[PDB]
Image 1 (spheres, helix red, strand yellow):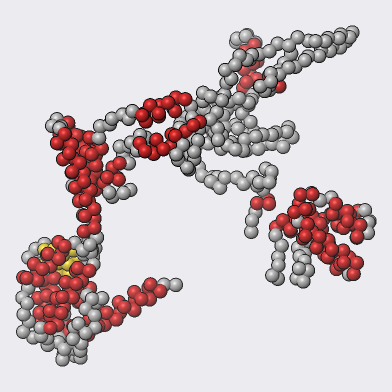
Image 2 (cartoon, rainbow over the protein chains, first blue to last red):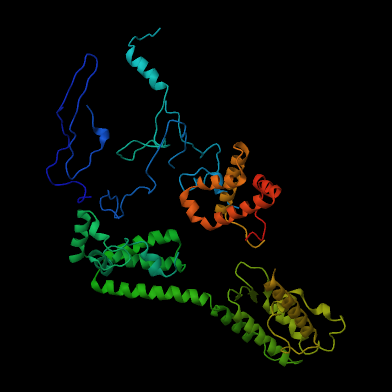
Length: 50
Length: 35
Length: 78
Length: 359
């Protein structure tokens, strides 16, 4: 099918997010990411990874 | 209906209504074939 | 005289199996699925162990009990 | 499948809902079809364009193969050739047309497909209508036979007309001549073949003089068994009074007619007002189980037991079956208040049903 599958507008396939916060301890680790989603798309969380 | 489907014919290619799914380790499965 | 209550329920709907399934098999013309798919003189070690692991496990297509895995295509080895 | 050689053909050289019927496609592509509108509006682009391109400018077709196959199939269904000969003769005719083709040839071919369609239909209806050939053969035989009988004549001509009617009224019957005789088979690939010439020769001497002698079996051996079969086959015909009664021939005809008659006839003859719905039974068993459980492991009073059971019910089913459940609860309440033995029995024994009058 041609129409109603892929948007013609410019749209990233893969996004890279920078950690907005990162606090380290002597044995552990911590990272906070501002996961953003475009206003006209859906994200399947299974593909997200570190 | 849907026009968003691969069409292998003039007729659309659509799977079974009943397709949404589950399995718990349990053995809550150990269930049979697609056939 | 309705036996639907005996069957497992898949949610407001009895899990009635196909009525077309009653056994029949003979010498020729009857074939069933799940076929027989499968001091070292040679020290490779590696592939060897891997191969032994492969030898003890399985794979095919009508193994559709439960799910095939996410996005899809329909394939062979029927 | 179908006998109409046009129909039994057109299944072979034709697509399915192509632009051979342009009107239906043009109706479906815009919006006009009401069975499932907006079907065409949502197909892939290529397909859509292609149909449209087909629709505005149709593509010409060559119908030679269709017509030739139609006439070949007509020949096949009319026993002009064997099916293997059909496969061969299709190519034969195709080459014949291809090496002499002209507009006149196509016109004659259309004429011919019409003619063969009509011919097949006519042949079928004529084969189911009475097989005039048998009638012609019978008339020839009767012309061979003399029409004058010195002893009795009304019975003879009445019987002749009866035989004529019999051969006319039952198709699939065969009348012909193999040797210097005429015969009568009641069906193709069928038994009961009567030597008509011999039967008439034997019966010539029994027409007008066997009436007084029918009482004594002194001349009964003159009837050869073949003629006996011939008479038996005409029992349903030549009804009472056609052949003068009190005659040996008439007596036999009457007996046979009576016998066959009883037979076909016999043959065509041949050969607690309120009870609960499964859902209500499930509810009843659940109520029994819950009330018994509460009353037996928690020691509560029966009224409180009934109250506790009620609440723990699925709200959708409880609201859906509010009247029946309410009536059952009230009945059990008053039973437990009045007759404890009956209440305990009815709350502890499966296979129990509410007695009539509870409704």
